[PDB]
Length: 11
Length: 258
Ligand SMILES: CCC(CC)c1nn(-c2ccc(F)cc2)c2nc(N3CCN(C(=O)OCC(C)C)CC3)cc(C(=O)O)c12
Image 1: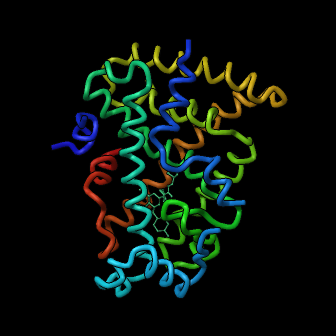
Image 2: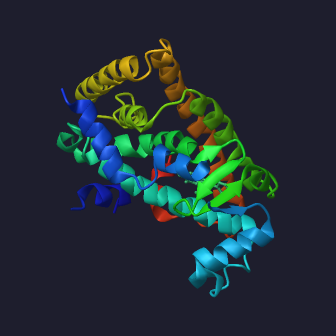
């Protein structure tokens, strides 16, 4: 969903 | 404690461009100042794109995509920088999203100043230099985008900050307790108080001759907010009236009702 979340959740 | 050292080190680790590197180049790169030199830069720096028909679309649209990709890269660096600011990793994910969503463009336009002088700005990882006049010469609305950023940068650069100051300034921007829709305001406000406190102490020793630097910089944060407000209005005009200027999805997310 949110691209900002994926950035924050990445290794 | 060592909060300021940790923030400076996170800045040096996470941003490919900074002021010291930029000034080495700004004091050589390839100068883009018309259609012709823009084409030469593209042919050598992004050969795969020139052979895929990118030189068919307008100069404005090509520069648009250059800038867009730069912002996208910088948002990634800013996210990694934020994750290394003591305290940020413990916040709720939604609060983390809010802080970045409303903070990244104030930070980007703060850091953009480092790669600018009065005549133009570095691009393409420091290998290109696009002139202020050339940007001014494009067709509306594109010629309207960078000019107020140059104006901000000239005054911001007149303060003569270095990277250690800029790193704390950017951290203060990101950890902003008055972003709309924040949940844990009291704790983020406490994070900002610490960052702003060490910034004031850092400016006192790093710039002992400019005793008024700290409130000047506080006002610069308000100027950046306004700057981003005006810039978002340019983004709508592009969203509404430009056919070949597709907004990157990450940026569409950031700009959704901001
Ligand atoms: C208004 C549309 C929007 C794209 C959705 C945009 N259009 N244009 C633009 C287009 C044509 C031109 F002729 C001049 C500017 C931009 N320019 C930007 N700038 C400039 C490039 N860049 C940088 O150099 O940053 C280095 C720093 C981080 C160390 C990022 C910030 C940032 C953005 C941005 O809203 O994302 C942007």
